Every structure is written in C-alpha cells, then in structure tokens.
Image 1 (tube, rainbow over the protein chains, first blue to last red):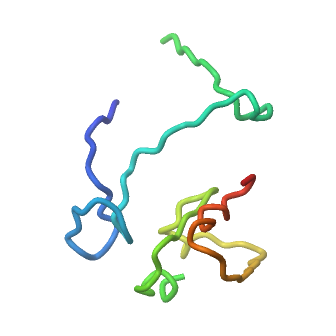
Image 2: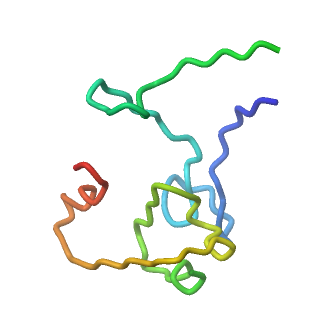
Length: 50
Length: 50
C-alpha cells in the first residue's frame, strides 16, 4: 500500500498545525546524493517483480 | 528522557540514527554527553562531516 498525504506530524500534546518547531515536524525528508559520498550511501535502483 | 523531552526551551533536537520520540523502550549500554557553547551561524556545524 502507498501513502502520499502530507500532514504535519503532531507528535506532541498540543493541537499544532504550525510550520516548524518542537513536536511540530514535517515528515518528509530529502535524500542528498553526490559522487564524493563513499560506498554504501550512493543511490541504488531497485525493481521488484511479483 | 521524559523530563529532558518535556523541557520547554529546547529549540533544536536532531537525531541521526533512530527515532527521537520513543527512547523509553530503547536501552543502551553507554551514554556519552558532550557540552559546549558556539556561535549561532555555526550551530548547523554540529552535524558530522561539516
């Protein structure tokens, strides 16, 4: 199953929508890739056949 | 970690290996704490490899 909804993580005890701060987190994070990175962190392409 | 977590004037609490909000169930054999005070501009420098 797949998830796309972009809702701010209200991981606190306060009704927080906000933008950023304590217990008010944007769930998405960005991969960063550059050739200077060592082996084990360069991107890998994955295909799964079912 | 609950008293540390619920300490209000914390601004930045960024982890790099595991989830930072459920440390109660996670147990470690060691805890290393290092302290200093730096400029605001280089606050982002605490990430490894800077």
